[PDB]
Image (cartoon, rainbow, N blue to C red):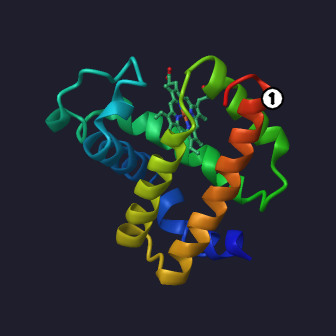
Amino acid sequence: ADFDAVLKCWGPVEADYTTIGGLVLTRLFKEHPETQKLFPKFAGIAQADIAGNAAVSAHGATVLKKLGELLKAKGSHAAILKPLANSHATKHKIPINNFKLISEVLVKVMQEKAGLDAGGQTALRNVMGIIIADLEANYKELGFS
Ligand code: HEM
């Protein structure tokens, strides 16, 4: 049910993955500046320059498309989630806590831009908690605690 609650507000997100994607990453980098340094292509870009950066927004669209494709799965997502754990642990080298940070940003962006109400905020936290716990379990299988 929590997946359905999120999907009932996904329309504004999917309508403009570039704009919403850029909002998410801009906010992430502003509020959690250590996360910017985990993107070598973006690390060192002055904060004031991020909101207008088309490459940042394009990457944010990639992220949100993948999250959309994890929703329109409603829990049965191992063929999507295992590769994401693999690349984020072994290629991008992203500590697990950073997924919690981007999830908090997404909740706020959806509250502001997508009509996600109090119950929907809780639903999204629940869904992101499922996703993050699966990433973490996969990280452990790879040797990353
Ligand atoms: C649930 C949230 C996230 C999703 C859905 C997601 C999704 C993606 C996807 C689909 C890609 C491209 C394919 C791949 O490399 O695996 C990617 C790349 C990447 N992600 Fe994530 N990601 C998430 C969170 C994060 C976080 C929190 C960080 C760092 C703080 C991060 C850092 C990266 C980096 C550095 C790349 C490579 C960018 C490039 O070289 O072009 N990701 N992510």
Residue 66 in the figure: left or right of residue 61: right
Classify the position of ligand 1 by quadrant: top left, top right, bottom left or bottom right.
Answer: top right
Comparing 66 with 94, the one in front is 94
Instruction: Tell me residue 136's x, y (percent).
Output: 69, 40
Can you say whether 73 is above or below 124 in the image? above
- The structure residue drawn at horizontal position 42% and vertical position 47%, both measured from the top left corner, is 21
Question: Which image quarter holds the C terminus?
Answer: top right
Please state if 35 lies on the left or on the right of 77 as rendered.
Answer: left
Residue extending furthest toward the front: 145
Query: Label 1 crowding class (10 Å Cα cut-off): few <14, some 14-19, many 20+?
Result: few
* Quarter of the image where one finds residue 1: bottom right
Estimate the x, y position of residue 18 in percent, counting from the top left: 42, 45
Residue 60 placed where, x, y %? 45, 41
- Count of numbered circles in the view: 1
Name the residue rendered at 58%, 66% in the picture. Answer: 124
Amino acid, disc 1: Glu
Residue visible at 28% across and 47% down? 31
Q: Determine the image quadrant of residue 82.
A: top right
What residue lies at 64% left-to-right and 48% top-to-bottom?
Answer: 132
Q: Position of residue 113 (x, y in %)?
A: 37, 68
Q: Which residue is mark 1?
A: 141
Ligand 1 within 8 Å of the CB at mark 1: no
